[PDB]
Image (cartoon, coloured by chain):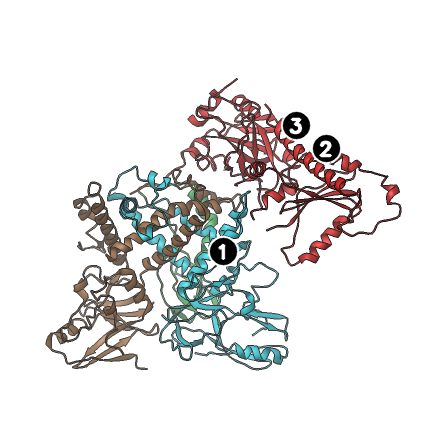
Chain colours: A green, B red, C brown, D cyan
Amino acid sequence: GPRFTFFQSSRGHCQIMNILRIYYSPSIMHRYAVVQPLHIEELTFGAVACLGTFSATDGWRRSAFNYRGSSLPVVEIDSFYSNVSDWEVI
Amino acid sequence: MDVHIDNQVLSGLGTPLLVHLFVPDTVMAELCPNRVPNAWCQTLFSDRTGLTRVCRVFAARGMLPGRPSHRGTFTSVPVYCDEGLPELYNPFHVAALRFYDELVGELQIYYLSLFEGAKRALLSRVPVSFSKTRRAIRESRALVRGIAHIFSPHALYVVTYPELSAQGRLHRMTAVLGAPEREFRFLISVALRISASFREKLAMQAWTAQQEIPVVIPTSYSRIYKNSDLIREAFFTVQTRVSWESCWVKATISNAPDACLWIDSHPLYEEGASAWGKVIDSRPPGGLVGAASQLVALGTDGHCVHLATTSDGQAFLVLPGGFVIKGQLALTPEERGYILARHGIR
Amino acid sequence: MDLKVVVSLSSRLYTDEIAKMQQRIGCILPLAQNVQGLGLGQVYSLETVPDYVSMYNYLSDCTLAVLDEVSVDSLILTKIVPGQTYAIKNKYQPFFQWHGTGSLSVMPPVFGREHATVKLESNDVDIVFPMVLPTPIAEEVLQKILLFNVYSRVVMQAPGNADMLDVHMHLGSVSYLGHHYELALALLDNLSLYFCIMVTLLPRASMRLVRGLIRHEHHDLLNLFQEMVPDEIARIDLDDLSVADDLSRMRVMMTYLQSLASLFNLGPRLATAAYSQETLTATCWLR
Amino acid sequence: MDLKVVVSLSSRLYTDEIAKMQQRIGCILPLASQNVQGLGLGQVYSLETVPDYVSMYNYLSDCTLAVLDEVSVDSLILTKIVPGQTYAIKNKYQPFFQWHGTGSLSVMPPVFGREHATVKLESNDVDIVFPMVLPTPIAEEVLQKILLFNVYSRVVMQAPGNADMLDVHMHLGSVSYLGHHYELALPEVPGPLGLALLDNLSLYFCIMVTLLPRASMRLVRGLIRHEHHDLLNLFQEMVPDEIARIDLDDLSVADDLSRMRVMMTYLQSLASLFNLGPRLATAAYSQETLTATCWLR
C-alpha cells in the first residue's frame, strides 16, 4: 500500500529524478520480487512533484505539533514560494 | 546461475544448444593475473579445420556456486559444431573461449570432457522468462559435477539439470583427433620459417651485428657469453608454445587498425615463461623519444632474448647486448586470414 | 510595465470581424508588430500542407499572447511573462472542461482546422488559435487521434486487418472526470510515421543498449531485475548488421525519440489555480 | 531582487589575465552558492580525471548560472540568473554558432576542447573553464552523440577483431551542421555518472520494450511493400528478423490503449530525463550587435 514522503533538496530542478531513483532503488526490486503485474498496470513505481521553493537563507526548524491526546514532532518552513509542478513518475 | 539464463536466450541465434559451466579460480589464475577478465566462443574443428563465426558468452565473476566446497567464476560454452542433427558428437574436438574484460587469457576445452560429465551429473501482460522460472525450482546439489580437464589438470564443474527439451535432447546424443596437433605444428612451422629467414639474413651478410639499438658492452662479453653462444637462439623455437599471446600475431591483427612495434621477450635460459605480446607505442605523448627509452631499456636487458615484429611486415631479433639481426615476416595470406579468423573478424 | 503589444491592421474591417473577436477575446494565440506573422497563420496557409511537427516546433519556438481588443484598425493584445498571472477563458470551438486541473496544455486544434481558424475576406491573415485543453484531456485525445490515423493508414494498406466499428466504440470517446466526450474524423499521418519508425527502431536499439549495459554492475539487484522482465523473442538478432548502418539507426532513433519526448510533453504548459464556472474563466500563470 | 554579486579573490589578478577576462565579458558562468575555488567549472573538470561531460553537466544543472559583467583587479562581479528577468548574452565563444532562427539557447560543458573556453588564473591555484552556449537542437544532438560514443567505445573495444576503432571517431565525428562541421572531444571511458545515466536510460528502454504497439509494425511493413520512403532509407528495402517475428499475432483495440498510455507517461519521463540542464528561451535576438535577450525558461 502506498505512502507519501516529502523531500527537501537544494539540488537541480532537472537532476532530482536521478538521485531519487537512486534513493528508492534499494526498496523497489527488494519488494518487487514478490509481485508481478497483469492486464498491464503496476509498472509506475511512485510519482513526484515539486511543491515549490523556500529560501536557502532560512532553514527548516523542528517544532512540536500536539493534539489534545499527545504530541508529534513537526517541521516548520518559513518564507515559502509554492509553485506546484506536475507529478513526475520515478 | 545467472549467466546460465543470461546467454540461453541471446546465444540461441548463433547456437542451438548452450551448456552451463563453472571455472574454478585456481585453474584460471595462471591464465590471467589479478582476475582481470570479466567472453567470445570460437570452436575449432579437429579434422575439418576451417573457420567459424564468433559467438558471445555472458560471464559474471565473483559469485559462488551453490556448493560451499569450491568458489569460482561462471561461464557457458556454445555447441554448434554438429551439423544438422546434433545426435552425432565429434570426439577429441576442442572448444576455444576468449574470456576478457578490456582481450586477456584463453581457454580450450574438449567436447568429450563436456559431454561425458553432462550425462554423469544426471491490456497486455508482461513477458516472463520461462527458462528462469524453470531454472529456479531445481536448485539442488547434484546439478553440478566435477570433471577433470585434459589441457590443465584440474576439475572443471559443469552444471546441467533436467530443464527443458533443449538439454533434453543433449544427453541422448552419442557417436563413434588432431585438434591440438595442428596449432602446435602451425606455430612451430612459422617459427622455423622465421628462423630460416634470420639464417639467410645472417648468411647473405657477414656473420656480424648491425646493432640497431645502442647499449654499452663489457670487454668480457665474449667470455661470459661464450663464442657462438646461441643456446637461447637454439632453444628459442622450443620456448614458443603460445602464438595468440605472442607478439608474432599482434602485428597481423593490427594491420587493419596504423603501425607500431611488438615484442616477444624470452629468459636467456629457463628463468620463467617471461612475456608475450607487448606494445611499443608511438601514439601517446611519450612520443618517439619515449619509445626510444623503452627500446634502450629493452636492449639493456642482459638476461633475456628479444624478438621484434613490426605491423608493416618486418621481423627483428634483438640479442641481449643490443645486437640485432634483420629479417622478413611475409607469409601466404591464406594464413593471414586464418589467424585473423582465429582471433576475430576478417 | 505594459506587457501589451500593439498591432496595426492593414485595411478597414466590418461587423462579423467584431463578432468573431468578441468570440475569440478570451482564447489565446502565439506570437512571432507585423500583421502577417501574428500566430499560426503562416503554417495554416493551404499552399503548403498544415503539418503538426512544423507548427509544433514553431509554437515552441515563439512565445504566447492573450488577445485583448480589436478596434477599427488596432489589435490590442498582451503577451505571456512567466512572472505574473493573467485571466484565461475557454472561448473554444470544443468547449471541453475546466474541473480544477492543475496542469494545462496548448496544442494546435486537431479536432478542426476551420474550427479555430477565423477568416476575413478583406484581410487574408487567416489567424487561428491553438486549442487549450487540460493535460489528461490532452493526452487522451492525442492517443485517440494518433492510433486512429495509424489504423486509417493501415486499413488503406490492407483493410482486412483493422475495422472501424470496434475502434469507434472505444477510440472515439474520451472520458475524464465524469464527463464523456465524443470526437471522430497528413499531419497526424507524418506524426504517426515518426512514432512508427521509432517503435520499430526501439527493438534493435533496446537490445543493443541493454547488451551494452547488461554487465556493467557485475552483480546488481536493479540491473538483473530489469533484465529478467523483457521479451525473450526480442534479444536475438543484433550482431548480424554492419557498424555504420547500426549507428545511423541509433542516431536517427535518438533524434526522433528526443523529438517525440518533447512533443509528448505538452509544449506550452499553463497552470490554473481557481476556475469560475459562471464567468467561464480561470486565473493562469505560465509554467 | 539583487543581481550584483561580487566574487572576492585573494591574490592579484595580473594584467596577462585581465586582458583575456575583459575579453570574456557577457559570457555565462556557473555559481557555487565568494571563495576563489568552486566558482566556475574547473572545480569539477580538472586535468586529473577523464573529461566525462556528465558530472560537469550535473554541476551545471544542479547549481545556477551567472553572467560575467565586469572584471576588476583583485575581485570580479557576477550577475545571477533569477527567472522573470531578460538577460542579454553576447556570443563570445570560439566555436561560433549563428543564431539565425533564434531558438532556445542551451548551456553545455566545453565538449569542443578545454582550450577554447578556459582561462588561466595564475593569481590563485585555480583554472576556470567556461560553459558552452548554443541552441537547443545542436545541444541535444551533442548529448546523443556523446552518450552514443560513451556506450560504443567499450563495445568496439570489446570485440577481439577490433580492426575498426577509428570508425566511430569519424562516423560520429564532427557535429552535424550545415555551414561548418565542428569536431569535438571524445573520452575513451565514460566514467561513473555517465554510466549511471546510461543505466537509468537502459532501465527506461527495457521497460518500454515490454510494450510495443503492433499497429505501426503493419504500417512499416506496408511501406516496405509499398514504395521506399526516404525516411525508410535506413532499412534499404529489408525486413529484419525481429519485425518479421513480432507480427505473427493479430491487431486489436484492446492492447493499444494501455500501451499508448504507459508510453505517454514513459515518454514524458524521458523528456524529463532529456530536459537536462538549464535552458534559455530566446526572443528578439539582435544580430547586428550579437545580443540574445533571454529569460530563464
10 Å crowding of disc 2: few (<14), some (14-19), many (20+):
few
Residue projecting furthest to the front = B204
Q: Quadrant of residue A84?
A: bottom left
3D distance between C-alphas at marks 2 and 1: 44 Å
Residue B151 in which image quadrant: top right
Q: Give the label on residue C259, or none.
A: none
Establish if C263 lies above or below D28.
above
- Residue D262 in view: no
Give the residue type at disc 2.
Answer: Val
Does dot 1 land on a helix, a strand or a loop? Answer: helix
CB atoms at circles 3 and 2 under 8 Å apart?
no
Q: Nearer the viewer, residue C257 or C69?
A: C257
Disc 1 and disc 3: Cα gap in Å?
Answer: 48 Å
Q: Residues within 10 Å of mark 1 (few under 14, many from 20)?
A: few
Q: CA distance from mark 3 to mark 2?
A: 22 Å
- Marking on residue D170: 1
Q: Which residue is mark 3?
A: B153
Labels 1, 3: front one: 1
Residue at (52, 27) in percent of width and height? B143
Name the residue beneath numbered marker 2.
B238
| Residue found 62% across the figure and 47% down from its top | B312
Question: Same chain for marks 1 and 3?
Answer: no
Query: Which chain letter goes with mark 2?
Result: B
Identity of the residue furthest to the top in this view: B176
**Mark 3 on the same chain as mark 2:** yes
Up the image or down, D270 lies above or below B79; here it is: below
The kind of residue tagged 1 is Met
- Residue A13: where, in percent of width, then height? 43, 63
Circle 3: residue type: Pro
User: Callout 3: helix, strand or loop?
Assistant: loop
